[PDB]
Image (cartoon, rainbow, N blue to C red; front, side, top):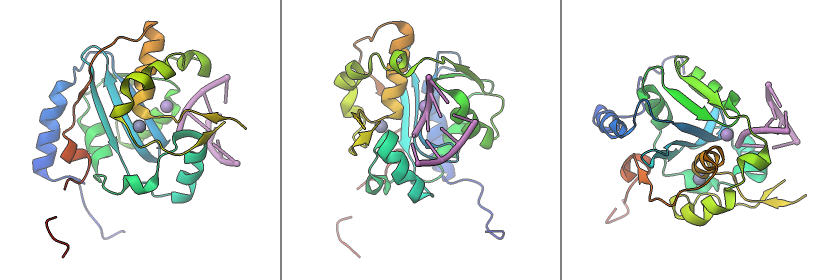
Length: 207
RNA sequence: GGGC
RNA sequence: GCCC
Ligand SMILES: [Mn+2]
Ligand SMILES: [Zn+2]
């Protein structure tokens, strides 16, 4: 609305906690970013630094629910009911807190660039690895094998017709890095954001 | 050819 | 199916 004037989706307390958590990100380490959903209506966001194993991973409820269902069928297969408990404002807050002039690597930078441009972050530099589907997803199976427990959102059947493994923003980052590095390391990853920041947590009585 |  |  024209009479609605809200600066942040998050409280100062939570913005301060986000600021501190994001000190785990190295401003100069290789950093992957991927999203599921349209750049103007993202539903899953991931950033990944292989050098430390740190990742940022969170979700967002879509506005265009009709487009979402169509995108789910052909790409991400995310159940929309699973996106209810998400934190609003988190996409903007994370992006706003990214280091100035950060270099982010991605596969098909067009959508990532639009999202970042829409958040006023034209200072961020983007490296596009511009691989084929085949080359970019060489380690798809090995990544899912090792890290499936890190995302449970992709339960829908995704079609290409032929059925395919759903696209996860987090698994994508990890497998794209594996492709470029020419191998997948066995290593335990670390979530940068606290769980209660990403999802609504826990009532002992209804009403 | 990419992306969802 | 929609986007570049
Ligand atoms: Mn992508
Ligand atoms: Zn996922």
